[PDB]
Amino acid sequence: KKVVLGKKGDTVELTCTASQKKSIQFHWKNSNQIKILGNQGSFLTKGPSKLNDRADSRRSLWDQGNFPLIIKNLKIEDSDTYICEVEDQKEEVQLLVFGLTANSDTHLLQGQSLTLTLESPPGSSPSVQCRSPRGKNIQGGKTLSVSQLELQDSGTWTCTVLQNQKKVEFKIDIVVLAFQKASSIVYKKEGEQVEFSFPLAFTVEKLTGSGELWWQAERASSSKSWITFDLKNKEVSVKRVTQDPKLQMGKKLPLHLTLPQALPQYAGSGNLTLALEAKTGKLHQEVNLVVMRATQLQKNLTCEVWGPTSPKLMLSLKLENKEAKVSKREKAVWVLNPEAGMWQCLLSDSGQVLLESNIKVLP
Image (cartoon, rainbow, N blue to C red; front, side):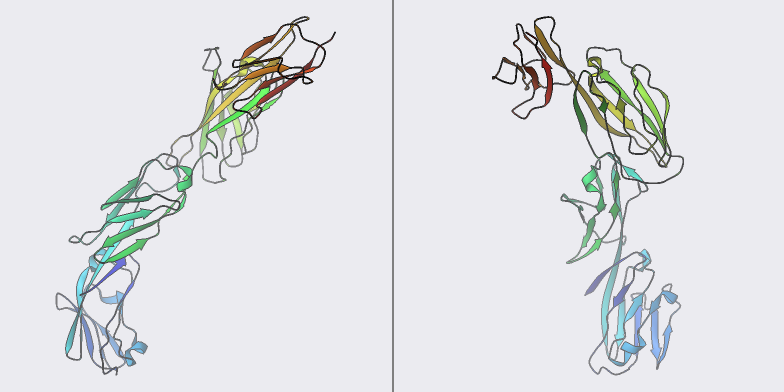
């Protein structure tokens, strides 16, 4: 019969009319033959039933035949078969509520799984199709959880509680805090003052955050090299550590890991781990630095690219004027015997020029 679904605490309207359309007697009673609410002229009445003061009917719409049932603050335990005994007939209506919910709530950063458990009348079965704000028609049973949340899954989802030839949609909001970059990469040359940047997405909250950046310098296994920082609102500050190079950091939230001069030994990978709280987790975002050193020995020259280079790239040295004085696939090429010209060292991959470092020859 009439199988209408509802949401917890939401409300729903049970229909009930008939021919004759005039203000006549009517009475809503649940399968337990208890009278939800009834009438006696304009005077609207209710029953002893648990539903009592949360049920209501529209007296205005009464004149036009409707003897509607409005249930406010939907209690899960409202799931029943109500009957609207109007002028010589009975209307059977089963109202099955539901309630989609995530327990892992407040301040979700990356990865940290999301879980969606469901409430439903003891004896009926749902199915949930959680459509994401972007793609993935993730679906499951009385429960379905999103694995490790990746940025783009931030927003407003739309899970659907299917039950019967009826279905009830649900709008849950899920925002993934995180970095706006995976592997940042900077290509510089022996000297060029290096800068790095990893942004977030504003937020407030109390006593909330600090971590540090770790670096794997090329060859220099001499690790444990780092910089530590504490954050609070639009305030950042180095906890301590740095040492080794003169890395300077900002006072302002949009973090700028600064590297005074791009010296050759400062090339390699790095992980900048951020970890705040309320209900913690730890963000990560990769960092990498490459260096190029164009320097003529004596009357003969050479140049080299250190750091995270690809076994797909090429290096080349030419005097600009004419074409390839030496082309190759490695990080330490040489050009013995150069001629006057403002020479260009080139690091790339495929075609688009990565690193370019100019230098002149004398005779």
